[PDB]
Every structure is written in C-alpha cells, then in structure tokens.
Figure: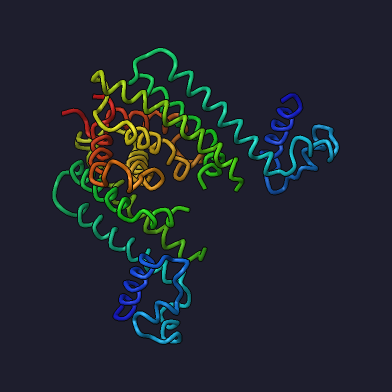
Amino acid sequence: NDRRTQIIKVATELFREKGYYATSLDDIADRIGFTKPAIYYYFKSKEDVLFAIVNSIVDEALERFHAIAAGPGSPGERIHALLVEHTRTILRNLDANTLFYNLSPEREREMRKREREYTEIMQRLYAEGVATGELLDVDPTVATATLLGAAIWTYRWYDPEGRLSADEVVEQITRLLLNGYRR
Amino acid sequence: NDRRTQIIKVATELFREKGYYATSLDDIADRIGFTKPAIYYYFKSKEDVLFAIVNSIVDEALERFHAIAAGPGSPGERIHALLVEHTRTILRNLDANTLFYNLSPEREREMRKREREYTEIMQRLYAEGVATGELLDVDPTVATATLLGAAIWTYRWYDPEGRLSADEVVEQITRLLLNGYRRPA
C-alpha cells in the first residue's frame, strides 16, 4: 500500500485533469517517477488502475456506513443518517456510480459482495425499528431496496450545473422518504 | 398497421416461446406465412422488430398514464394512482425496462421524448397538490424523479420466483412512498 496508494492518488488526479481515454500507464509512471516495468508489478493496465480507484471509494464509503449503523441513536434515526450519507456519497461520486451499474468475473463478484453488505446493514436496522413501532410495517427487503434505490437514481437525473445544489437535493430527498409525499 | 401489428404480435409470441437470439426474420416470416422479401418492406432486421415491440409497449403505457392524470380525483389521489400503475407496468415488463435503460440516434431521441412526457405530467400534478396544501413542499422535479425512480429500481432487485408476489411489492412500495418510513408521532 505504500507506493500503490501513491499510484492510485496520482492516477485519480491525472484522470480528473487530463481525462481517462487521454491518460495511459506511461503517463502515470512518468508523474510519480517510475519506469514502465516498475508500474507493471502493481498494475498491468489502466483498467486495473480504475478498478483499484473504485474499490477504494467503495471501501471508504462502506466504512462510513458501518460506523453510523454501529453508532448511537434509535434505528429510525440511524436509517435517516445512513440515507443522507448514501445520497451525499452518490452526488459526489457520480461517474463512479454510472461506472458501477452500467468484465472480470472475480472483480464483479467482489462488487456484488459489497452491495450485499450495504443492504444487510440496513435490512436488520429496518426490522428493529418496525418491531418497536418506530417504522412503517413493510417487508425490510422492500423498504431497503426502495429507499436506497430512490437515493441511487439521482445518478441518472442530477445535473451539477443546474439550479439546485447537492445539499438541497439531499435534504429534500431524505425529507420526502421520511414523511412521505402526502402531508 | 394491418399486417405490421400481426408481425409485432407474432414476433412477441415467438421471442417469448423460442428466445430472441434463437429467432430470426426467416422464422417470423414463416409463422405468418410471408416471404423473406415481403417482411423487408415492414422490417429489415430483428432489432427493428424489437424496437417496434418496445415502442408499442411504451405507447400503450403512456396512454394509460395520460388517462389517469386527465381523469377524476385530487392531484394527490392521481399521483398515487399513477405510481401503482407505473410500478405494475414495470413488474410486468421487466426485460423491456432492462432493455430501456442499459444505438440509432433518432430512435434514442424518441425514447427521450417519451421519458419527458411521463415526467412533465407528474411535475405539473405535484405542483398543484403542493399549492393547495395536500402534498409535501419539495421541488416538483425532485419529488417526481425520486418517486418514479423508486418504482423503476425494482427492475434491478425484483425476483419473480421469490416469496413476495407482484401485487404485494406494488402495494408496499406505494404505501412506503405515500406515508414515509417513520410512523406518525
């Protein structure tokens, strides 16, 4: 993880400023000051670098998710905190989300395992809140996929250059799902 | 539309029973009793037949959407009726939805135009319900994309061979979005 993290960070900066299709492994090797053979040890293609960047963003997001679910508050308060966090993470990593839902079997298997963790943390938390009378009595699997699904769909419609900011969209979405649309 | 509708129906039945990749334009022509040259006049590829099937399903779904939005009830009652209808249509046309969201510019442009109509019917309807105090005061565009988005996402998670039926999933989703997840204090 010493030079590898340095390689992921340098690659992320370089894909931002230059663009993914204009950037090669030769360019990444150049910026950190490594030879072409030296980068092969860590990464054999630019696609393997892109997987590493996405798996890192998925790994941190999932840590922030566990901390909230394993921390203080009632299940209904934790459910709310998880949705604000999840939507914030979607709006800030829009290209990563389009990349996540639109190759290598074992790498795909790893993505399916992380999706399962998100869902299961919230499933158990929705069942506890329903058992104590705090949450709407619907199946936990249906509520979890619908609430998370409502947050995720923003990647297909949210325009960063539009009138409403990321903070306004997160607030309204989370207020809509919490209270419902009927006053 | 005389033989064309017959061709779309025969192609739909044949893609169901046999499968899309195992069915050719020669097979469709055989079933209706037409020559290979005779089918070219109406359709030049199996992909063009598949577009026609999808554009038809989108065309009927959108007519059922307009009827509810242009009929009786308050805006909040119509909003509810539209969501039950929309989700029912998703669960019944699961392969069409996966095909809709995952080629020909003008054909894509047509799909974008139909998506816009759905959204605009509900946008205007959410603004009226907010203006009269019936609906939660949030931006119409955000509510509409979120509510429809919640209904659409079912195509990625709903398992027809699972424990819950299509009717239970529609009822619970529409009850969740209406009342919210937190029970009234």
